[PDB]
Length: 29
Ligand SMILES: [Zn+2]
Image 1: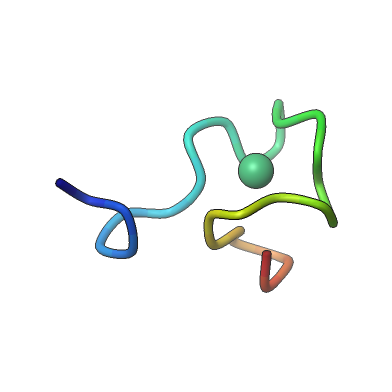
Image 2: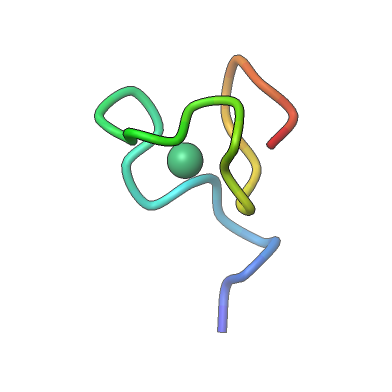
């Protein structure tokens, strides 16, 4: 439900980092 509302699911822990589909706190996606 919060695909764009909330930030990435992990963000800092996320493995994608730059290749993430969600919105990051420091990166765009
Ligand atoms: Zn991410």
